[PDB]
Image (cartoon, rainbow, N blue to C red; front, side, top):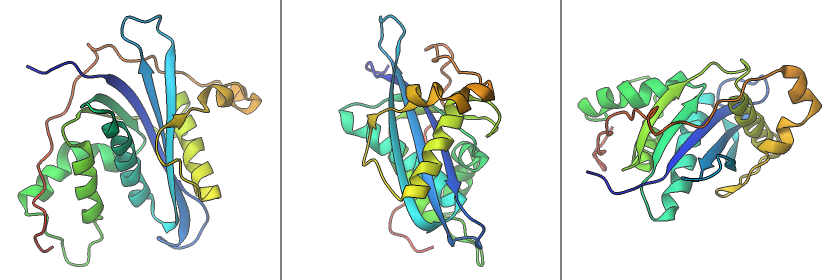
Length: 211
């Protein structure tokens, strides 16, 4: 069995701003990472990671949320166990189902389709050897961490900034805002290593073949 690894809970969102046609709007991806010290008092340590593109799509940004998240945690010398919660069914269904279908078909594109296949391959690689439980929640529905992540995504889109990796979180300050309070949101408690039900490992991509 497996050597000890850390457990984190990740909350991701994406957003585009504006009303231009698909692919013309600025966009952002926002990620909150929660970490509770094993044996600790239960206080949550939070870090944020965001990126943006000036003309992009919601699907692309959703994929970047995954890639950026897993890349940042990947840099700590260990595989991780991750509970990844997002508003994007595109990500959840893709990671749990579709990538397997795509791999099965040789990662070949369908003509006329725009499936973001290159990004999916990057995302699958980013996830790597980490063990992930993929979870969906509705957006804009009162899940506090999800709403924060959205706030981060929008900020990223608006400012056209990037964190470059994990940075100290703004969650606590955001949580205390009057706007946040009026929303009457619900916080998700940190997961039990019992709550942890990872998905199967992803197909190792067949790099270098034509679409």
